[PDB]
Image (cartoon, coloured by chain):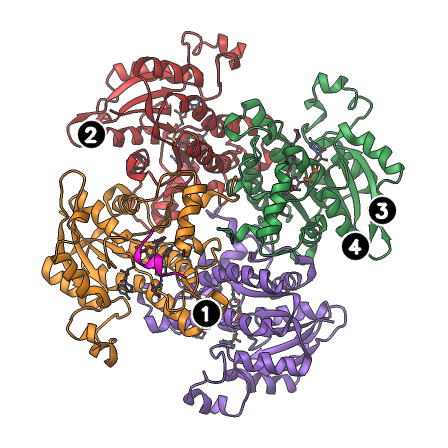
Chain colours: A red, B orange, C green, D purple
Amino acid sequence: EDICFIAGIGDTNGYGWGIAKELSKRNVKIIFGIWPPVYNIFMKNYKNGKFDNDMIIDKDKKMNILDMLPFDASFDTANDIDEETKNNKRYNMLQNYTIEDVANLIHQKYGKINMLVHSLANAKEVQKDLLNTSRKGYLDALSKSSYSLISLCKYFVNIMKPQSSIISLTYHASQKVVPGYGGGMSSAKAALESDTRVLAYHLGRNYNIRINTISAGPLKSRAATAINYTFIDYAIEYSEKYAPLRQKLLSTDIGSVASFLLSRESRAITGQTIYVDNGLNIMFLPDD
Amino acid sequence: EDICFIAGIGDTNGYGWGIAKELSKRNVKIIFGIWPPVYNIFMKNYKNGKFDNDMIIDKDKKMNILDMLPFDASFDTANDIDEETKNNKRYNMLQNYTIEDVANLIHQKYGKINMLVHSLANAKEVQKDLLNTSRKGYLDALSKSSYSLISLCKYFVNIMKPQSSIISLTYHASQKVVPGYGGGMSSAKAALESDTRVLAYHLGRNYNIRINTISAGPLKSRAATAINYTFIDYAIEYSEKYAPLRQKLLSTDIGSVASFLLSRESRAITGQTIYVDNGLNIMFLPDD
Amino acid sequence: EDICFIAGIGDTNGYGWGIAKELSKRNVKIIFGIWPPVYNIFMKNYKNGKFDNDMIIDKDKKMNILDMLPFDASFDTANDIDEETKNNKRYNMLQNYTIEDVANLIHQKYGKINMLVHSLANAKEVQKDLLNTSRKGYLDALSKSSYSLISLCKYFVNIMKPQSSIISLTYHASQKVVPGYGGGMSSAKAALESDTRVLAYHLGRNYNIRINTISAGPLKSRAATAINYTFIDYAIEYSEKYAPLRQKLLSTDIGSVASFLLSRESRAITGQTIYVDNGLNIMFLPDD
Amino acid sequence: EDICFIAGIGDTNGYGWGIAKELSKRNVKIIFGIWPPVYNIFMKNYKNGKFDNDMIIDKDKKMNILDMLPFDASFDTANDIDEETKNNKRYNMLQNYTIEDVANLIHQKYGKINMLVHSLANAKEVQKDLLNTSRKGYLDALSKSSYSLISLCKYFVNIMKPQSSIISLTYHASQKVVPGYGGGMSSAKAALESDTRVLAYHLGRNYNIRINTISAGPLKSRAATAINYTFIDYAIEYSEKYAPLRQKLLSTDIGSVASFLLSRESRAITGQTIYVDNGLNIMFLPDD
Ligand SMILES: NC(=O)c1ccc[n+]([C@@H]2O[C@H](COP(=O)([O-])OP(=O)(O)OC[C@H]3O[C@@H](n4cnc5c(N)ncnc54)[C@H](O)[C@@H]3O)[C@@H](O)[C@H]2O)c1
Ligand SMILES: NC(=O)c1ccc[n+]([C@@H]2O[C@H](COP(=O)([O-])OP(=O)(O)OC[C@H]3O[C@@H](n4cnc5c(N)ncnc54)[C@H](O)[C@@H]3O)[C@@H](O)[C@H]2O)c1
Ligand SMILES: NC(=O)c1ccc[n+]([C@@H]2O[C@H](COP(=O)([O-])OP(=O)(O)OC[C@H]3O[C@@H](n4cnc5c(N)ncnc54)[C@H](O)[C@@H]3O)[C@@H](O)[C@H]2O)c1
Ligand SMILES: NC(=O)c1ccc[n+]([C@@H]2O[C@H](COP(=O)([O-])OP(=O)(O)OC[C@H]3O[C@@H](n4cnc5c(N)ncnc54)[C@H](O)[C@@H]3O)[C@@H](O)[C@H]2O)c1
Ligand SMILES: O=C(Nc1ccc(Oc2ccc(Cl)cc2O)c(Cl)c1)N1CCOCC1
Ligand SMILES: O=C(Nc1ccc(Oc2ccc(Cl)cc2O)c(Cl)c1)N1CCOCC1
Ligand SMILES: O=C(Nc1ccc(Oc2ccc(Cl)cc2O)c(Cl)c1)N1CCOCC1
Ligand SMILES: O=C(Nc1ccc(Oc2ccc(Cl)cc2O)c(Cl)c1)N1CCOCC1
C-alpha cells in the first residue's frame, strides 16, 4: 500500500508531473505539494478539468491524486515564516504549508508515507551570471533549491516507513559549466548532488532509507521558459542535435527512472547522481 | 516477449545467474552463453536437477531458459580459433562458439533479440599486482575482460532490434585503487567504463541501441574466490560494515537493476556507469 | 613586480601561512587579510615577534609582509554590515574591512595586485551532522565559505592585472562523504569546487584571469582543532597510515603547489580542483 | 643536478620537446629515448643544425641534451624482440633499445636518475572507430600506449632515487567521448589514467616515488596530424574558440607543468590526472 509526496508543482509541464504519471502506473498514491503563490490557481485549474487529459495513464487508469496541499520549501517551521508573507495576498488565506506542517498534515491523514520526491528550484537571479550574483541572491538559491532537500528529509524521515526511498532532480551545470545557468543554481545543484551523498550515509545508516538524484536533460517546462531566444530552446536544440540518443526526451522518460529509484527494485542504490539525459553528459566534442 | 543473451555463466553463484532470475520474473526468455572449459559440467549439473532449487522464483515461477550454448569471448570469428584450442579436449566436441558464430546460431534459432548481458571478466596474472604484470598477462586481461564487449557489440547489434539495450559488469577499482585487484583487472575495468561511453555514442546514433554498465558491490562468486581467507571475504566484510546500507548485497539486487536497464524504463539512460553496491562508493573515510 | 592578497588568517598554523612562505621564496609581496575579531591579537602578536621564527625562509629571506588589514568575508560592502557587529567590542575600532573596502585600500596604497588567495572557512554548526543542520546555520556556511570566493573575484577583478591568477582551498568531503565534516561544510566546498569552474569561464573569457582550487590533506591547524579525540587527529592518523605517500603533509606542501598555480608557469590550467593530499584521494579500500 | 629520460621524441614539434625545453630551463639534464623507425633521421637532422633554432631557450640557454638513445616501448627485455624486428633494416644496426636495456644503459653511463617522462602513444587502427577496431588492433593500442608505462616503471624504478617523479601524457577522450579518437586510443588513455593511480600506490608505498599524468589540450604534432583538414585542426579551432582561456596552446605550456610535477614543488601530488588544456574540459555547452 503505497504513498508518495511530491514537493514542487505549479503546473503539469514539469518533471514532478512526469514523475507522478509513471508512479501511477504501479499504483502509488500521489500527494502534491504546491508552492502557495500558485496553489489556488492550480486548484481552480484542477477542479475545472484542465489536467483531466494529462491525468490519463496508458492503461485505463486515472492518476490517483490522494491530496493537494500548499507547501513552501523556504520555511522549515511555523516560526520561520515572516510578516510580509504573513500579509501576502496569496499566502494569507492558507495555513500549515511549512515543511514541518505538511509532514504533519500528511502523516495525520494517511499515516506513514514511503516515497519522497524533491522536484523544485528557485534562484531569484538565475537571470544574471555567477559573477554578478548578489549574496542575498545566491543564498536564496541555496536555501530554496538545496537546503530544502535536507530539510524535507529531517521532517519526513519521521513519517516514513523503513526501506523508504527519496529522490531529487539535478542538472549537469554543477559538474560542467553551462553559461547562462546563473543565479547560483549551478552552485545550488552541486550542493544538492553532494548533500545527496552525505544524506545517503546518515539516512542509510540510521533509518535504512535510500536517497538518490536524477540528472535530467532539458525539458521545455514552465520554469525553464522563465530562464532565458530562451536558453532552454537552445539546450533542447543542442541536446536533440548531439545527444547519443537522437530522440526527444519526455518528462516521463524521467518519470520511469524515478519510479524505479523509488521502488524496492533498486534497494542496492544510494547516494547516486543518475544521469537521465539521452546520454548527452558523456560527450566532449560536437560532431560538427 | 523479449529475448536476452547472458554471456558468462558458470554456475548459479554469480551475478549472471542473479540477472537471469530477475529477468525471468519480468518474463523475458533466457539464452545462456557458457565458457567451454565448464560447459559440460554446467550441462550435466543442470540435467541432474542440481540447479532446481536455485531456479525457484518467488511468485511460483521457474526460469525460462530458452537455450544453453557453448561460448568463448576470446574468439571473434572462426578463423580466430587457433589449431590448439580447436583440438583441445574441451573445445573439440563443441561448435559455433565464437562471438560471430553464436550471434548467428541465436539468430537462426530465435530471430533478432533485444537484450544483451556481458557478465565475464578474466585475467591471467590477477594475483600479481599492476607493476608486476607482464605485457602478455595485461593484454590478455584486456582482451578477455574488455574487448569482448566491443566485439559482442559489433556482431550482436545486427541481430538486435532498435531500442534494444546492452549492459556489462564493472568494479569500482577502476576509479579508486583497491590493491589485490591485479593482473590489469583494474585497467580492463577502466577500459570497459570508457568503452561503455564511446559505444553508447556509436550504437546510440547508428542503431538507436543503449549500452550501460553496472559497477557492482562484492559477491562470493566462483571467480571472486579465485583472487589471491581471500580478498573477497575481506571485501564483503568491509562493505557490510562500512557501507551506507548495511544489508547483505545479493546478486538479485544487481539482477533487478540489470533488468531495469535492459527494459524500456531506462530508455533515456546510456553510456553510464551505474553503481549497485549499497552506496559504498560515496565513502571517503570509514566512520570507525 | 609581484603582490598577493591572502584572505583568511588568524595565526601561523594554517595553510594561508604555508602559502605565504612559499610565495616569498619567489619574491612575492604578501598582504594578509585578518578576520577582524582576531586582527588586534594577531597584530600585537606580530609586533611582539611571535612569528619572527615562522617568518624565516630557507634561503636567508624574511617573509615580505607588505601590509596587514582587517578583512571580513561575510560583508560585501559597507552597506551590508549590521548594527550588532557595528557595536561589537572587536569590530568597532576598525574600519574598511568589507570585501570592497579592502579591494580599495590595497589598490589605493600599492596599485594593481596580480595574485589572489581565498583561504578561509566558517560553518557555525560544523559540530552537527548535515541532517541536524539548521537553515540559518547551513546558509552562513555557504555565505562565509563559498560565496565569499565569488565576492572576492568581483571586487578584486578590478584591481588585478591581466594574466593574474586566483586560488582557493577545498576538501574531499564534497566529493566523498566524511562523517563529522558537518555544518554544511561539505555542501559549502562542493559549491566552491563548482563555482571555481564557472568563475574560471567568466574570468577566463572576460579578463583573461585564471582561477583554481587546491584539495588539501588534513593539517592540524588552529581551525581543524576546533572541529572535533578531535576528528582532525583521526584524519591525519588515517592519512599518514594509508595515503600512498607515507610522509607527513606540511602546510608548505600546499604552499608550493599554490605558488605554482599563482605563477605564469601554469598559464594553461584553470577551473581545476587540484589534489594536494599525499595521494589519499585515489584510494578505495584500506590495506588492513 | 637532476637527470631526466624522455621516452618518445621524434621531432621538435611535440610535447616531448616542449617538456625537454622547460626542463632545460630548470637546468635538468636530458636523456632522449627515440623510436628506431625515426632514430637515424632525428640524429642526422640534429647534426645538421636543423634543431638549433628550436633549441633556443629564452634566457640565452641552449639545451642540455645529455644523450639521444634508440628506444622502443613494445619490448620489455631482449628476449622479447622477435627475430623479424631483430633483423629489420632500421632495427639491425642498433642495440640496447628495449625498456630494460636502456634502463641499464642509462644507469651505467650516468647512475641513478630522478625524473621520467612518458610521451608516447600508438594505435594500429586509430582511424577506425571503437566498434570497428579489431582485437589485434585494440590490444596493440593498449600494449604500446598504456602498458609501456607500467613497464617503463617496473624497470626504471631501480635506477631512480627516492623522491623521484614520473609523468605521462593523456587525452580527455578517456572521460567524455570525442569521436575520431579511435583504434582503442580512448581505451588506452582511460587505462593509463587508472594505471596512473594503482602505480602511484605501489611506487608511493614501496619506493617513495610519485607518478602523475597530464591530460593535454590539442597540439599540431606529427602524430596528431596522422589521425584521419584532419581532426586535430578542428580540435585546435574548437579549443581556441570555446575554451575559457583563448590563448593558443603551446607545448611549453605543457612543458612547464611537466617540469613542475617532476620537481619537488609537487611532492604531495600523486596518482592525479592534471589537465593542461586552457580549461576546455570544464565546459558542457558551447556558449555560441
Ligand atoms: N526541465 C528542465 O529543463 C530541467 C532539466 C534538469 C533538471 N531540472 C530540475 O527539475 C526540477 C523541476 O523543475 P521543472 O523543470 O519541472 O520546472 P517547474 O516549474 O515544474 O518546477 C519548479 C516548481 O517548483 C516550485 N517552487 C519554487 N519555489 C518553491 C518553494 N519554495 N516551495 C514549493 N515550491 C516551489 C515552482 O512553483 C514550480 O512549481 C528542478 O529542480 C529543476 O532544477 C529541470
Ligand atoms: N563477484 C564479485 O564480487 C564482483 C564484484 C564487482 C564486479 N564484478 C564483475 O561482475 C562480472 C561477473 O562476476 P562474477 O563474480 O559473477 O563472475 P563469475 O564467477 O560468474 O565468472 C565469470 C564467468 O565468465 C566465464 N568466462 C570467463 N572467460 C570467458 C570467456 N573468454 N568466454 C566466455 N565466458 C567466460 C567464466 O567461466 C565464469 O563463469 C565480472 O565482470 C566481474 O568483474 C564481480
Ligand atoms: N587543515 C586542514 O585540515 C584542511 C584540509 C583541507 C582544506 N582546508 C581548507 O583550508 C582553508 C584554510 O583553513 P586552515 O586549515 O588554514 O585553518 P585556519 O584557522 O587558518 O583558517 C580559517 C581562517 O579563516 C578565518 N575566517 C573565518 N571567517 C572569516 C571571515 N568571515 N572573514 C575573514 N576571515 C575569516 C579564521 O579566523 C581563520 O583565520 C579552509 O578553507 C579550509 O576549508 C583545511
Ligand atoms: N598532440 C596532441 O594534440 C595531444 C593532445 C593530448 C594528448 N596528447 C598525448 O601526448 C603524448 C605525446 O603526443 P605528441 O603529439 O607529442 O606525439 P608525437 O608527435 O611526439 O609522437 C609520439 C612519439 O612517440 C614515438 N613512439 C611511438 N611508438 C613508440 C614506441 N613503441 N617506442 C618508443 N617511441 C615510440 C613516435 O615516434 C613519436 O615521436 C601522447 O601520449 C598523446 O596521447 C597529445
Ligand atoms: O527559479 C527560477 N528559475 C528556474 C530556473 C531553472 C530551473 O530548472 C531548470 C530548468 C532548465 C534546466 Cl536545463 C535546468 C534546470 O535546473 C527552475 Cl526549476 C527554475 N525562477 C523563479 C524566479 O525568477 C524567474 C525564474
Ligand atoms: O580472471 C580471473 N579472476 C577473476 C578476478 C575477478 C573477477 O571479477 C571480480 C570479482 C570480485 C570483485 Cl570485488 C571484482 C571483480 O571484477 C573475475 Cl570474474 C575473475 N581468473 C583467472 C585466473 O584464476 C581464475 C579466475
Ligand atoms: O568554521 C569553523 N570550523 C571550521 C571547520 C573546518 C575548517 O577547515 C577544515 C579543517 C580540516 C579539514 Cl580535514 C578540512 C577543512 O576544510 C575550518 Cl577552516 C573551520 N568553526 C568556527 C565556528 O565554530 C567553531 C569552528
Ligand atoms: O598511433 C598513431 N596515432 C596517434 C594518435 C594520437 C596520438 O596522440 C594524440 C594526438 C592528438 C590528440 Cl588531441 C590526442 C592524442 O592522444 C598519437 Cl601520439 C598517435 N599512429 C599510428 C598510425 O599512424 C601513425 C600515428
Towards the viewer: B187 or B149? B187
Q: Quadrant of the C terminus of chain A?
A: bottom left
Residue farthest to the left, as pictured: B109
Q: What segment is highlighted magenta in the picture?
A: B220-228
Residue holding disc 3: C53
Residue holding disc 1: B133
Marks 1 and 2 belong to one chain: no
Type of the residue with mark 2: Ile
Marks 4 and 3 belong to one chain: yes
Mark 2 to mark 4 CA distance (whole Å) = 70 Å
In percent of the image, x 60 and y 35: which residue is there? Answer: C146
Q: Position of residue C136 (x, y in %)?
A: 57, 22
Residue farthest to the right, as pictured: C48
Residues packed near mark 3 inside 10 Å, few (<14), some (14 to 19) or many (20 plus):
few
The image quarter in which residue A226 lies: top left
Residues packed near mark 4 inside 10 Å, few (<14), some (14 to 19) or many (20 plus):
some
Q: Position of residue D237 (x, y in %)?
A: 50, 59
Q: Is residue A237 magenta?
A: no
